[PDB]
Length: 299
Image 1 (tube, rainbow, N blue to C red):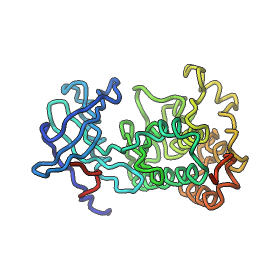
Image 2: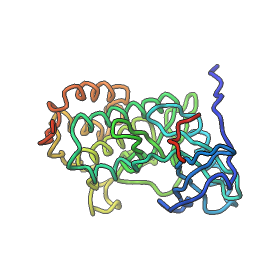
Image 3: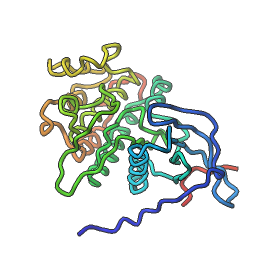
């Protein structure tokens, strides 16, 4: 009793796209840069390519196709879309590559030029995007400043659905079974019970905001992951960013509550920030404030 998906999954030939440089690598495989040159069309399109490690792992080969499915079905202005998929022996994913890298790497550069009206807008956008996902019953499981592409300083998008997971008509949570996870970004509940919910993503959002407000600082710096859980159970959290009014930090604090039902909801996170974004100066203290080829969107 739902709507038909109709999302298009385009298949690409290993010859339609080249790899320029590697961007990251892990137990999954590797993510290269390179550009795509559609069949026939005389236009180069910079994209990101995620290739696997081995084409013999029924587990990874299944998850990879899952990630494809979800990134191919999402249709939001603040969520990256999959461009195509290459069913080569080691399945490759071809997605959008924002011309400004990730929001994390952005703020660590323009930190001395980043105003408030901007930071608050990014908060709005990310939330808008996540809320969209909540509607699709999706759980990013991997929100972080590192996983937020920058299409333009006035427009950012979410990506990386490696860990992402879909929910069952009745299912309200998802239980995971082992596999590397970013501890310093996940809810206490996802550590003590490996449980992941929409409210768990809210937690990650918090942490993500902190990064932005800190201009890319590293959370729980040094403090190794093999204790966070204990730190958290001790009521300890990330400190209040100097530039942040109690008004803002509070939203963050509410994000990192033990009771998942006491944390804010992406629906309301959008209103809350939206409000603030109208009077940024009254929420952020950032002295000096007032001071061949295509894009990827060409159906």
